[PDB]
Every structure is written in C-alpha cells, then in structure tokens.
Amino acid sequence: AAPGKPTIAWGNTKFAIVEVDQAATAYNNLVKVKNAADVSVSWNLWNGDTGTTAKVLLNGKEAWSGPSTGSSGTANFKVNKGGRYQMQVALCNADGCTASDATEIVVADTDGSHLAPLKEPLLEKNKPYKQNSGKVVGSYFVEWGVYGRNFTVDKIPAQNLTHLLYGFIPICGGNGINDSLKEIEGSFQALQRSCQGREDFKVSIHDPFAALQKAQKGVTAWDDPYKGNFGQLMALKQAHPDLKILPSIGGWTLSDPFFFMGDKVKRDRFVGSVKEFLQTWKFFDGVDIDWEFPGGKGANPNLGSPQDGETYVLLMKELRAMLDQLSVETGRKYELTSAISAGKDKIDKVAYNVAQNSMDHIFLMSYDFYGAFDLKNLGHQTALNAPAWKPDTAYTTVNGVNALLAQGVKPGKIVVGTAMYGRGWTGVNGYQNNIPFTGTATGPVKGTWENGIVDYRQIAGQFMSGEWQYTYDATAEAPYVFKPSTGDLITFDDARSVQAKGKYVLDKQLGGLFSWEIDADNGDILNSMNASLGNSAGVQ
C-alpha cells in the first residue's frame, strides 16, 4: 500500500527573496538581495508507512525530494519567484504517493508579488477618473508625511494618477556633500547613520523606519518583510500595475551631491547605485532626478558651477543607458524623468533640447515663483500668466514652457506643475488699487507645517471664510486670499487655475500635469487636474 498521509509541521510559512534585517540601521545591512528565498518545511507521519521518498510540492511541482527515513522529516530548498504557493509534502513508494493537505507559503519579493492589492476607497473630495486622456497626471508623495501630516500610501488617490513620485531618495555623503541637510534638525545625522559603511555618491534610504518598518495598512504583521511606505507601494503596484512609481532623487535639501558629478568617477558610482537600487526595489519604474539646481541658487549658497549644464546632460544620457540595459534585462519599460526649475534664468543653464532625448518626462516646477523668501517683491507663486499690474513678470508658467520650447524641447515632453499648497506673507502693506501684490510684507504667513507655506486643504478649510477676501485673477489665472486686518496674503492654485493649466496643456500639446505634494490636497486639485486634461469620470 501507498504511504500514510503526512501532516505538515507547524512552522514559519513566510519567506523572502530580499531579506530585511530588523536590527540594522545602516542601509548596507538593512537589505540583503538573494537569488532565491530559503524555504524550510517539516512533516510528521502519525499513521502508517513513511514511504521511501519524500517530496515537497509547490502547486503540484516538486521543489525538493529526498529519501523518507522515518516518521518526521525536514526539507530545505530555494524558491526563486515571489508569490503565494500551495505547498504539500508527499510520501511516495512503489505503490503510490500520498499527499498532505496543502499549507500556503508566502514567498516575498519587492515587486509585491506576495501582497494583496492595496485598493483603498477615495477619501475627502477625491472623485474617480479614468486615465484615458493619454496625458501625465502626477503627484509627489513625501516619505516623512507619515508622521505629523499622517498621510500614508493607503490615502493616495492612486487611481487618479499616472505617475506617483516618491520624495526623496538621498545620495550618501557627509561634510561638504550634504551640508544642506544640516539646516534640518537631525536630518544630516540620520543620513550618515543610514550610509554607515557605504561609499559617498551611492543612493540610500533617508528614513528606513518610514520607508520600510513602520506598520501600515496591509503590512502590519511582524513578519511581513516590507512594511512602511515601500511595502504599501508594492501592494499599490499590485492594485495598479500601470501606475508608474518613480523614486525621486534630490529636492531642496538632498541636491548637494549632484554638484560633484562632473567627476565621472562619482557619476558612474551614482548611476551604478541607481541600477542596484532598482534591481533591489522592483516596484519602482525608473528614476526621477530632482537636481535643484544646475548652476546653484538652490538651498546651498556655496555650490553651483558653469559645468553643471554639461553634467546634467551627461547624467541623463548615462542614466538612460543604464535604464535601457535594465529594460532589456527585465522586459520592462523604465522611465527617466526630472523635475526642473521653471525660471528661464535657470532653464538656459541646461541644453534641454539635447537632454530631452534621454528623458520620458520633464516635470516643470511651475510653482514657488514668489513666496516669503522675498518680502519685497510679491506675486503669484504658480500662475499661468503675468498679472495685469505687472505684464513683464518673469516667473510665470508660460515663460518657463516658452523657454523650453525656444531651446527645441518637444512640447509633449513638458509636464506642467500645479501646487497643492499656497505660499504667503503676513503684514502686507502699502499696496495700491486694492491689489495686495503691489505692497511689501513684514514676514511669512503662519504655515501649516512650516513658515510661509499652507496646505491647500487648510486654505479651503480655514481661509475661505470670515474676513478673508477671495479673488480669482483671470489674467494671471491665479487665486489668492487676503486678510486685510493682519495683512496675510496667500497665493495658491485652485480648481479654476488648475483647469486653466490643463486647458493650456491640451491647447499647446504638452505632456500633462503634475503636483506637489499629494498629502496637502483635499481632492479639489487632483480632481481638476484629471478633469481639465480630459480624463473621463468613473473607474475602469
């Protein structure tokens, strides 16, 4: 007779191809990419003949076999593809094979193949849109937004985006390399910890706890290998396979390392680390480069060189070469994007007509034109056009688009930026003709999280009532609110100015719209981005 029916031993059933060390603060020690998960299974036989061969099956396919030598056994084997498997132990002899009941085993990998889809309901005012315009609809999600802002990946209105950018992946480096981080309490020291033992100019993760370990919806079990933002983003990719999730490298305080990449030793090390990063974190679909900015005038006053243009172009060419190689190794399409200044003063430091050939999308940062960093010269921070009181205004969206077009940039590359925040001043005074923007300010408006910057959610929730005036400037295509008694002036985007940008995108055959930052919207801005680009209401 065939062997008795084995009983699978209670034991760990959760395994990982990319292992995460739970007592490691250095990125080098935190993650270990294996070629396969090490899986183990044991069994007991409570009744009968133990057979002469034991086998471990996954969905009916042998993953291990060995001699059956008594009433309990253990098998150790490798599984090289993530997912959930129905695992059986079979005991076999010449008279037949007898299989256990199946036990599910989970084999984790960083494409999220082991995860249920994170398919969460739309919150606040977000309404469902189909991505059927063919236009980019992008937004940034910030790693640190899971703390005070309490805005986690399960709150992203992900069906209403084509592109989700993760801000920010840092480049390792200490003194003189990431000095802009020292303005933020503990930030520099947190990167040095993450980068311990890791070469400068390689990418890392700035806050490993937020990115990988913090419990979040869908990834709360202790032995779920990938938690935090990355584990939720993996589950999000399972829900939305065509969503492009891009790691963004740089931004205001993590851009200092780019200024050294005129040394090809450093640039080659960076590009190789990006390749390794995308081989490690398979849910990411390419890379976004947010170097602020070639030529300087970003956070650090001591960086910027005339060579930065050339470095920027080389960097894109080389990143594209790496991503093309990764693309044919994987069968996947990878994207290379960059967020760039929208001021023509900064645009003309780069040959974007050359760089565009390496790039899928240029995210034109048509915001922060004005703000509490200048108390003398007030203006619309994210307007389409100049206002009627100052028709020579330099920093407008159209002038940034026009500067790019004047270089030879194809219109379809350019994605226009929308702000899900306002910037503002207090004590605005000495203005003429009831236009507060012809005055001067005494300081920043009291912001939501930091001085001078207000979430759009708070503008709509608090500053569109009481004493606040609301004006839509139809020449500039820009809303603003003004409190006359405190001189508080806030300049932002609203549904109408976003609609004007989206119509302008369609008229000029531009690439789409993107936004900073997704946690600050209540739904009104992203709804308008979708509607104004021609996306059909509904779900597919």
Image: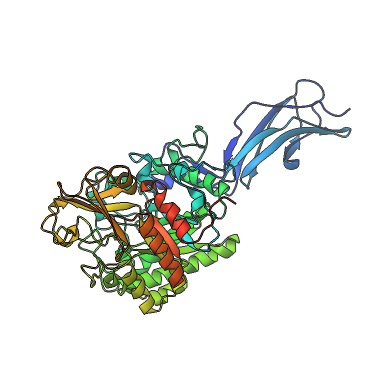
Side (left or right) of 449 relative to 73:
left
The one nearer the camera, 276 or 357, is 357
Which residue: 40% across, 50% down?
Answer: 524
Instruction: Locate the N terminus and report the quarter of the image it occupies.
Output: top right
The one nearer the camera, 499 or 73, is 499
Which residue: 63% across, 47% down?
Answer: 81
Which residue: 51% across, 42% down?
Answer: 19
Answer above or below: position of 52 versus 314.
Answer: above
Judging from the image, the colouring scheme is rainbow
Q: Position of residue 370 (x, y in %)?
A: 23, 60
Q: Position of residue 15 (x, y in %)?
A: 58, 38
Residue 269 in sight: no
Q: Position of residue 418 (x, y in %)?
A: 37, 58
Side (left or right) of 312 relative to 358:
left
Residue 536 in sight: yes
The number of numbered discs placed on residues in the rendered structure image is 0
The one nearer the camera, 519 or 222, is 519
The one nearer the camera, 18 or 371, is 371
Q: Position of residue 8 (x, y in %)?
A: 70, 28
Residue 62 occupies quadrant: top right
Which residue: 27% across, 45% down?
Answer: 463
Q: Residue furthest top?
A: 47
Q: Residue furthest front?
A: 433
Side (left or right) of 177 relative to 61:
left
